[PDB]
Image (cartoon, coloured by chain):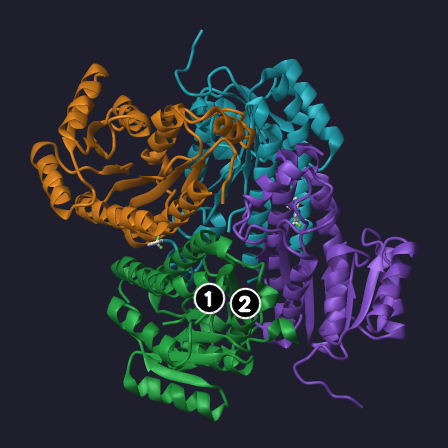
Chain colours: A green, B orange, C cyan, D purple
Amino acid sequence: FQSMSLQGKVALVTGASRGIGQAIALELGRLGAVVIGTATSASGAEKIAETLKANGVEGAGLVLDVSSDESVAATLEHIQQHLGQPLIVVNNAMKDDEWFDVVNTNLNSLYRLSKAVLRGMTKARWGRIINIGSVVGAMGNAGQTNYAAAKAGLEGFTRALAREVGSRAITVNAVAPGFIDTDMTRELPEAQREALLGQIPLGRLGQAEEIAKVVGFLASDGAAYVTGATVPVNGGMYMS
Amino acid sequence: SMSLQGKVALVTGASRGIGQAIALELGRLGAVVIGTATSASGAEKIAETLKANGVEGAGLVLDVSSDESVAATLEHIQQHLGQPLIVVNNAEWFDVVNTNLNSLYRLSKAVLRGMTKARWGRIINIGSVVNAGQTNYAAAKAGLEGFTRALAREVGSRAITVNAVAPGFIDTDMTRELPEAQREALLGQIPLGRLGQAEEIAKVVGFLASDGAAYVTGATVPVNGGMYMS
Amino acid sequence: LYFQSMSLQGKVALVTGASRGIGQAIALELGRLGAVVIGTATSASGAEKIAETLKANGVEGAGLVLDVSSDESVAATLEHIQQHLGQPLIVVNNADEWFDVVNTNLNSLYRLSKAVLRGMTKARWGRIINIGSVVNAGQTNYAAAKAGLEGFTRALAREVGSRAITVNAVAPGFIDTDMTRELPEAQREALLGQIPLGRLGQAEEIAKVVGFLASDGAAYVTGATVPVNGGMYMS
Amino acid sequence: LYFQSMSLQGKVALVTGASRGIGQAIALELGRLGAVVIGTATSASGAEKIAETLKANGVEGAGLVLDVSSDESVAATLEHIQQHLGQPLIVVNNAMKDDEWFDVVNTNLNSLYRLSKAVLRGMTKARWGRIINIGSVVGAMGNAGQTNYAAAKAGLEGFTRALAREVGSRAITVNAVAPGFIDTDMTRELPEAQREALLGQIPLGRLGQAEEIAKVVGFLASDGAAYVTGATVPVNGGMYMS
Ligand SMILES: FC(F)(F)c1nc2ccccc2[nH]1
Ligand SMILES: FC(F)(F)c1nc2ccccc2[nH]1
């Protein structure tokens, strides 16, 4: 199953200590990648290292703050010294008037991390950038507004970046999850969980593994002609 | 009737092309019109154009990238004419789009106070006119659409509408000197087989500003003769 | 004589499904804008009612019987209109099961559209405006009808564009009718909570958008679907 | 007595239009992933060629004659597959001027519907299914081709999403793959100077291979894609036409 092998590649997965990010990190490791998972605390990083080890995945856990040029540059250097250039990068890391700052800040962080890893990918003439959107289920109209805004911004961003870097055989894609069984979602009020479930044609929540498998495919050689795409993974619930 | 009499309209980037035609269309509908430019020369020209067409208002200097210029300009308008209740925003892909949306946000938030007091408003965002160019164009359009929809959601309960107009190939100063080969290829992609006039964008704007469009919000109306670039 | 200074003076407009709600309001708006209006219904009773409504509002035109599913009724109604009033250059289409519904409706749009295109091609001018349906099983049907209508409208606009005919659609959200006014208080409040403007739309608010799309000012708008939904977007 | 885990082994897949290009590559990819594959064509000649291609590649299955525009041919074909091999739980539907778009799209969607409804009964009883619709590749070069292409894609997206909704509660997914410019007969025979302008519209700077579509289909068919439904995955090297 050679079009699925990630053997020989180094993959950076931001926000990898739990839920979707962790499952992505294990799916890339299982496919044969060396995996570097990041968290914002030392506690998170150590826990990533442990989870990788317990699953036989070589790599590391480390601390990365995607909002800081310094942390990004420093982290990339660490990865280069110890393991080599990451050619697969997965970016995974409420009031009504706050949607603008959240989305703007997040896209600025995708941009900052994407640009820093592009140089290595340009040299290698090969790359995979995969952006993970946010999980559904924020409270109120404020939550639906923020959710729709983040998704539209992510789609346009992903498509433009794919265009900018395409000639270098780097693909850029996104995955837009729906209602997925995670820490955040299990702790939602039961009424809110039940109302969201009632809107899912498949009649169940997604597993974190079901996002990871899509990411694993996008990282593979078999997805080499897929770029600029946003793959929704939402059991048929399309929230606009 | 569908008169804009008694309303004050601010149109940014109003010294030429699409912005100037929007300014005159709102004036023709009876609005008091404040048009902006980035130089004193632009502002003066706007004032002269308005006068020559019988439109009351003013030309002024506004830099949408500066909090200070925005706050100051609005203050001048408020002292002298009242709150603008109709605002039309007409003034490396990543930096361009990010900068522009941060500007829409900045201007939009400052004019929202006046609109919230009046319980009524119209915000209309004008997208940019039609590989590097296609990428930039598609990026600016996707960002504008999501932005317009989200802001509409945030201000809707206050009877303020927020909409966008996405122009295609329009006859302006930028487009008037494009090489013949590029013009011909573009025409071949336009079902109506011609460029749009600046007036044709202005009429869409004039309708979105009206009472009849009061249930239209969050929309991006494409005005492109049937040429859709994604 | 008496000449309106409104945008549609001198034009003949056909509005299908005009005996109530959205269709009736579109018919009166086009009339108010100075068009001669032909409104259609599927029964003689509907047609007569349309005729009475138009007269009562000072609109010149007629109410007629049209079945958009029948080639014959279409061709025949068009001939009658051209003989008695002139060529209609403005046409507004307002007349588990989701597939049949959408497929049947798009086949009807195609049939009516093709028959009126000959008059519009001779005049080198036209407006075709398709009205989508008003808002689980209901959301699926609604999203399907809207996606089909959007792709259809854009493809037809491409096919006829070189003739200075525009083709556009209007996609309504929740509009105020008897069905909606009689919803229980809890259900109506939950509904309004999904609409940023916090209210239902009036039929007139759809009609004003149609009236604009029909005007000379909208000459460069084609292939578009203008949502009129108070900011509530479902797909 | 072979009990599979997380694979297509033992699943029966029906691939319409499987005698050449995209369809054939899909049929071999599903075979390689362990499915029993039934590939269809509209002629006996096509069917025979499918049978031979499957055999030569070590895939179990069959080539058959199916006309997706005919209720009779559909019902009859499904009956034959049921009697001899079992219910197909994976089904892949793969089977100029501006003014032809309506007939093409209307005919094709009616056919997706007809085939999809007939296979749903088997999938409902199994509580498991995969329906994958393949869009059309860019067909000619100017306006007429772009119109037709964009129309077929918009129809396919809305159709896929609505059907996904209708059948979701039965653990059947419905998805689509929208190819761009793929290396085929239509593309190979075209003028050389026009090929360079075409590539200039594709950020990856090349045409896609049929295998690159087949791999996306193979993933959508798998257990790992169980929460993907209603989606249209574009496979176009970054060239988006609408
Ligand atoms: F519209 C929006 F979702 F707020 C957004 N912000 C952006 C910032 C940079 C690039 C695209 C963006 N899109
Ligand atoms: F949903 C549907 F009824 F199948 C349909 N029919 C169509 C015909 C032409 C374009 C889109 C279409 N969508």
Labelled disc at residue C41: none
Asked whether residue C67 is in view, the answer is: no
Labelled disc at residue A130: 1
| Quadrant where ligand 1 appears | bottom left
* Circle 1 crowding by C-alpha within 10 Å: few under 14, some 14–19, many from 20: many
Note whether ligand 1 is within 8 Å of mark 1: no
Q: Looking at the image, is C50 positioned above or below residue D145?
A: above
Residue placed at 38% from the left, 38% from the top? B165
Q: CA distance from mark 1 to mark 2?
A: 8 Å
**Closer-to-camera residue (B22/C69):** B22
Asked whether the beta carbons under mark 1 and mark 2 sit within 8 Å of each other, the answer is yes
- Label 1: chain? A
Say which amino acid is labelled 2: Leu
Asked whether residue D31 is in view, the answer is: yes
Which quadrant is home to the C terminus of chain D? top right
Q: Position of residue B167 (x, y in %)?
A: 41, 35
Q: Position of residue C31 (x, y in %)?
A: 47, 24
Q: Looking at the image, is A116 positioned above or below residue B222?
A: below
Residue matched to label 2: A218
Q: Residue furthest top?
A: C1
- Per the image, label 1 sits on a secondary structure element best described as strand
